Amino acid sequence: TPFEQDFEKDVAATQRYFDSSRFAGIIRLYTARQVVEQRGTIPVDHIVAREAAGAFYERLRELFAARKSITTFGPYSPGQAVSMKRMGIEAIYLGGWATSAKGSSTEDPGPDLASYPLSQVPDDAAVLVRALLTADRNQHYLRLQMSERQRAATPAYDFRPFIIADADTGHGGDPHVRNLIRRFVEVGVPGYHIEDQRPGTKKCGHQGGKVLVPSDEQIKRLNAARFQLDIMRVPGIIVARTDAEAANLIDSRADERDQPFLLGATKLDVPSYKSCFLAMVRRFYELGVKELNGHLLYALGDSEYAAAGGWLERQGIFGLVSDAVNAWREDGQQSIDGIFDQVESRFVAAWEDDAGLMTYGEAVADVLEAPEEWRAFAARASLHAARAKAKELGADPPWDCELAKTPEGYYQIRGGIPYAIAKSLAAAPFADILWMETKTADLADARQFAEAIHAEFPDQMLAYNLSPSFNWDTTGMTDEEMRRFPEELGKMGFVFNFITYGGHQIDGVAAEEFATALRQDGMLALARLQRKMRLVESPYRTPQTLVGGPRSDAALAASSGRTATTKALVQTEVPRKLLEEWLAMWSGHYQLKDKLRVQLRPQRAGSEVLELGIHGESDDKLANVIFQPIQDRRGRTILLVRDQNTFGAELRQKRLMTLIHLWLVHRFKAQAVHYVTPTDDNLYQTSKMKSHGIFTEVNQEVGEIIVAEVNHPRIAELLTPDRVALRKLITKE
Amino acid sequence: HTPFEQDFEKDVAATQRYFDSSRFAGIIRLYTARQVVEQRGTIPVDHIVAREAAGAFYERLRELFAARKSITTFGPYSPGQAVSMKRMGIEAIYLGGWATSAKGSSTEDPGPDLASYPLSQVPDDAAVLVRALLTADRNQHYLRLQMSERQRAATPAYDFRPFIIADADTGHGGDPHVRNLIRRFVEVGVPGYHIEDQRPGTKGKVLVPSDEQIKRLNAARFQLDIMRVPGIIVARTDAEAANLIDSRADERDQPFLLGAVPSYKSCFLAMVRRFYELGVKELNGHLLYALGDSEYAAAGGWLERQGIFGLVSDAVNAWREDGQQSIDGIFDQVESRFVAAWEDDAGLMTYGEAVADVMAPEEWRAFAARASLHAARAKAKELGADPPWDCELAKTPEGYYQIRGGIPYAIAKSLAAAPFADILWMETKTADLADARQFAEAIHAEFPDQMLAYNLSPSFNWDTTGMTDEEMRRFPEELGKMGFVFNFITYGGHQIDGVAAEEFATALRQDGMLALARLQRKMRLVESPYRTPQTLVGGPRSDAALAASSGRTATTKAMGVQTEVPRKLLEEWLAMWSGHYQLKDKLRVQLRPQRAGSEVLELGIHGESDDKLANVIFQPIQDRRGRTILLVRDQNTFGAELRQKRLMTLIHLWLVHRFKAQAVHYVTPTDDNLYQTSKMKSHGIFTEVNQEVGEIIVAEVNHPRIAELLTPDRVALRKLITK
Amino acid sequence: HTPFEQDFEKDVAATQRYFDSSRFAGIIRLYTARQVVEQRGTIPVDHIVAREAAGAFYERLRELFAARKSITTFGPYSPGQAVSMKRMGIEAIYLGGWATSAKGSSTEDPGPDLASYPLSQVPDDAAVLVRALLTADRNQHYLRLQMSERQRAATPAYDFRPFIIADADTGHGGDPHVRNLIRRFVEVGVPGYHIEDQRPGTKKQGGKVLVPSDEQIKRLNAARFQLDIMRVPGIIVARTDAEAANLIDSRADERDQPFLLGATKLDVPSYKSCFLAMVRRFYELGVKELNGHLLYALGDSEYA
Ligand SMILES: CC(=O)SCCNC(=O)CCNC(=O)[C@H](O)C(C)(C)COP(=O)(O)OP(=O)(O)OC[C@H]1O[C@@H](n2cnc3c(N)ncnc32)[C@H](O)[C@@H]1OP(=O)(O)O
Ligand SMILES: CC(=O)SCCNC(=O)CCNC(=O)[C@H](O)C(C)(C)COP(=O)(O)OP(=O)(O)OC[C@H]1O[C@@H](n2cnc3c(N)ncnc32)[C@H](O)[C@@H]1OP(=O)(O)O
């Protein structure tokens, strides 16, 4: 029947899609049929996400093969996202941290607990996608107005939405994951990252209490994600993150893959950690601190309280409680917060110490005093399997992991890179990119991970996070090592590397500076910003054009049939064009035939150190000057020159650099020029420039500094608009 | 009287007292206390955030108005920016439609400021700011409770009250739209709102009549009264730059109406039809109208006589010559010449100007300026003047009347609105104190107590004004003197957000992770809260919440380097110095940029009273190989009795160590500077010292001697201080 | 011709064909194919739900028009009601501002039909209906796949295509507002929209204010422009409220001028003057409540 044919057709199409190279080495826990059953009859098409996912994945694969990588950050505004793409960053990251910090109209801003509605990050992403798509429409409108030559001169930016957004833990089970993924796709996001934490379990300001889930639950999240993406015909990029490097807890011991990393007590005559904790709290309560009534949460038996009480007595913890409660009364019954913390820390240490906390592998290893054969077996063995092997070998050490459980019921695990590897390997067949969460930026830790993964999956693309809070200047790395760090990640197969909430940070610094500047220097604060924007030729210079006014006018013209009523320059800096005209004379006299362009930008971003460059038709830098203007206390300006070049030998001793100096002196109203660590050429140059009368006086501490005082009469003479004196200078008359 | 009637009378009385309070002195309501109470229903509501903010914010503005002072602010583009400006000590916040338009939302594409977003858009934006501020306050207060009383007197507490004036555009329609818009602002906690006298969706600037503007303001006040919020209503006029108005009905606008030949409309459509007929199919705007043959004929005749049809032929030929591309540019050329021709021939002027051409001259001008059309005609006919004047003839195709925009019209509008508004605001493009004065003086002549507001366009090129840097610095203070109490850089946040993103993206591609290192260094130097971002967003208070929620059962415990030479080092050296010369004064070291975001630093030594005893304004510079030089531009040991005791030598030792300096350059040194550096050479701090008297000192650092002095035993250092 | 120029010319040609298709027979556009393509940018988008619904829905209406037949429907107040009426075999759905006003939202108090809600309000309502219909279809189709061939022939399959004509009120302002409103409808899958010739925020029998025909036409043209950009052949319904209207906010348009009322006894003072004078008398006789005259600055001569 037509009905059956339509079905078989889509199943076949879906099957081809499944079997395409895109999903090589990917396992699905469902059939093409199971996907088509969900799709209904009325066509839908999430084209933005579909096309973005394709190009973005192909591009990452390309960079993986070349051992290169994208290095990006999280934009905190649509403007920031559009800006990054102009500056030529290929892809964008969007994180839950910044989403948490920003809040919304109904969500108070706060810490990254992923406590917002699951719609929060997609809602944020939607703004970025609309910003990018709009930027593209505005760019394309302007480019249509341009001539072919203008189009080859002005650059076209790539505003495709290559985004990998934060899906947190999935915000629940499979219905939550699918809903979350659906919301991302619908707004055009092609990439999503899911971590192996338990939801609503995150702590701030502690180096403890990070709770993982079993690997089977993580895998089902990834599989659920893939299912949803398949239904929607979007080849979305699934990033599987593990938090196992820094984790201490897991909410279940059911999965065999996690059981090697379970910690347990070896001294079994010790009472449970839970019992001992609650007994300690109950003692505080009984001694009269009514505040600490946490024990009322549980219904623990008298036998357990007794046993636990005995242990706390022996170890002198009950002693510390008495002392603490007495200190509490002495102070005069104030916040117990600080005093309780003191006792708890000492209690935890005492329990850990006495209980003999280790893995089952470590426990059986102690009884065997081959050693290294066992470690390898333990690391890949379930609990039931490891016990069987040990008993066969005549080892049967006392080991109980139930005894080490927290009050909530979370089991303790040995966090570290080995555990991160174990988890990531299990997840590799269900994910396109793997990511080990890290606090510390360290290439050795990254290598350990990357090598272990690639040993079993040579084609597995990776991702590396860079915490904005991590103090880089405590690593002891050189500036040059810091510069190369992103490239070193790329070499190890980490293709997508991100400064999570970079946008949040730069947004803050900028607001602080401008607010301070406005109170300090009034409207000069805005003047200085505007100057900065003109120098780098920022689009924000003309903000009406930036947001898309030209295209909007066009729309109004179309809407109104051109009936809508539309009827009713002072120089701020010495223009680059002036030097280009001088270089036209110079190029003429020496008969060079190369049209010379002048460029003046900061040598690096947001630097006071400028670089003037002379560029040929091939865009080769013929000459340059790296300098920085400095004012004295009265506002008198000095040009400080750190480097200069007329790179071509056959362009030297023709006063090319003298023309540049004349422009720089005029542009910056310079009274003097200081050359720091001059060369021989520099001594010869400045001495002759003194003879031509550009400088009145020239002092030279050979090898260290040249100080050249400007001859203002002679500058004025050369700058006369008739260019008589200037023509003589160029021709050497 | 029944309980029902008593409850009513009570609230009416309470509402009447509220009406009559000094807060609303000189304010006219077009409704009674009864009319407000009958809207309120039975079930209590309380918009406390907006209510309390409005009270404090209004009192504060009144305070600043009487002292001839003012708040100078900008529009934050993020909740972080809004919280930041309050830390930096800015008292109030502006929120504008421009930035809201530019940002967009999950369902709104970002774009130009046409106020084409849903009326909920700006309130939704404001809600984030209010929540950010309220949360900042809760986080601050939590931390301050943990502090001791001496820590609380040491650390400063910032004011995070939501003093916001948000953009209500044109009101987004009639009274139901205005009330809905105001309601949405109040519900999210905004205490101030600004409404302009434009026609919606016309952003060629079209005003509305003053009666419509007033009804918007009155509608706003009504809604605020219902909600028991003494909200700050800002009445803006766009009449300074306007050319059109969508009605001639209001008497207050009639003095500014321009009037005249065939109608401007007929002549325009005939011109367009000619382009169409000559073969430019693109220009078919004439199909919008059903203009009669008689009108087309008349209009055609006029265009022929004046040679406009001539210009069309020429234009269409140029269009074909180029090769039939966009007519946009060519049509504009012709339209401009056409407009000029029509204006010229029609004799386009106000009715006052028309009768003036035909009682003294100056007596008439004064009468015309305050007279309706019917009134001005009556007076003229009585005086035996009856000039030909038709304003219908000058109407645009849409039907908008033409008006004489300018500061005089802005004044006329603002004066009519003054009894219904708390703050008046003349929209301006150009920053100009003379234009501001003209406005301020005219308003204050009739309303001495009327508070004003001044907008500062981010796009306005300040360096084209010809003002000095010092004049630019004083501009905000000069506004404050003329009674402009609230002055704002509309979308400042948008601009600074952009520059920051450009720089960091460029920095990241240029210097990799050093781009982040440098940002972090900057944050440490100014001691920014963003240094510890976990604390900033409110982690400490969140942990407390988790402890309460869990009864301290939730597991938080586990089982199984100096980045810069610290200021403290110098403080310890100054403790030795203070000791030897027996000063009782504990000396504090401060090193911040001399002005915001500058490479030029200022090290300052501060006493217990926070008086600056000494300072050094310097800036580190690298050569091409990375070698560092300290460039000193100024230096002071301000107290004469603290001089020649090697105070400045200790500071230099620290600066040289902190910045790994190989040399020190002093630019435009004084005599004291020559004496100082010469003696510092004798103590061995410098190896060589060259001095071009009055111009520059170059001092090369003696690394052996620096290392010696920095030895942790401080033997050499002790000798230096005491000798 | 460069690849850039070729891609442009291609889309303009495609757009021109679309313009000239029979679908838009007798329809005037005040803009060119070029002016539409200029707006579209580079990155593909596709509003397929609205596009396909618009096609089928328009063809079906044309069919019924030629047969002198019609769809008789109502406005569903819930997604359940919308799905239900399709089961009962009603072909198309209406969605009105009245019900949207009466229902309110999480931030909008329910109230009279003044179209004072944000312009996003009715599209937000429509989005629920479209999702309800699309979901009903997916649920139906899932069950029908489980059924045998015989069962399929037995049990009827309902048509849950989103044939909706939704209320765009007056356009909620000028062309930017209309285009934004239309865009929001299309994005959620609505293929039909109705725009009336009233002045916004003017609704109250009597006191019904119309706008000139040139302004109404520009709304419709602005709507068409937006639909063309988005490649959706959307059904534009032009409503007139002129049957019961008494007022118009301008006399500029020639088409309305035949219907203008005027005074023939010219020795009578203006209606405005007489109204304000009446109110001022109440005020002067001591009713302080009636101070509406303070809104205007009417001269002494006019008051006299
Ligand atoms: C700035 C610093 O602190 S680092 C030192 C700068 N950079 C370098 O040393 C890199 C190598 N050097 C160079 O590239 C070039 O020689 C530069 C940049 C120093 C000078 O560039 P040029 O284009 O040659 O300078 P320009 O032509 O303006 O020279 C000005 C005068 O000095 C003369 N001059 C320049 N270099 C020399 C030389 N090596 N020997 C003799 N005379 C010289 C020129 O002939 C000219 O005088 P003239 O026209 O009367 O003969
Ligand atoms: C920095 C520029 O670009 S120009 C700005 C210069 N600033 C001023 O002129 C402001 C007023 N002057 C001053 O405050 C001083 O010049 C300052 C800034 C040097 C501060 O002075 P001090 O804190 O006394 O500097 P300090 O004591 O470290 O001087 C180092 C040596 O020079 C000596 N010295 C300082 N001033 C004098 C002087 N006027 N005459 C002789 N010797 C002097 C000191 O005694 C010391 O040597 P000694 O103790 O072995 O004899």
Image (cartoon, coloured by chain):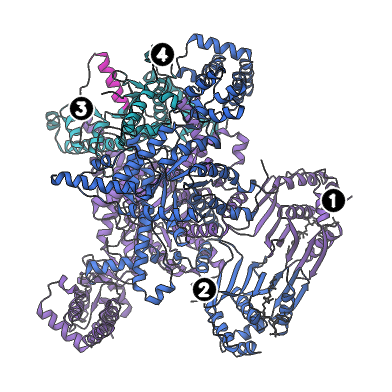
Chain colours: A purple, B blue, C cyan
**What amino acid is labelled 2 in the image?**
Thr
- The secondary structure type at the circle numbered 3 is loop
Q: Chain of mark 4?
A: C
**A317 shown above or below C86:** below
- For mark 1, what is the residue? A729
Percent across and percent down for residue A596 are 72, 46
Q: Is residue B352 left or right of residue A457?
A: right
> Of the residues shown, which amino acid type is indicated by label 3?
Phe
Q: Nearer the viewer, mark 1 or mark 4?
A: 4
Callout 2: chain = B
Depth order, front residue of A269/C202: C202
Report, in whole angstroms, how far the alpha carbon at label 3 lies from the one at label 1. 88 Å
Q: Tell me the amino acid under the disc marked 4.
A: Leu
- Rendered residue at 46%/17% (across/down): B287
Q: Is mark 2 within 8 Å of ligand 2?
A: no
- The chain letter for the residue carrying disc 1 is A
Q: Is the C-beta of the residue carrying label 3 under 8 Å from the nearest atom of ligand 1?
A: no
The residue furthest right is A733
Pair 3/1: label in front:
3
Q: Which residue is mark 3?
A: C74
Label 1 and label 4 in one chain: no
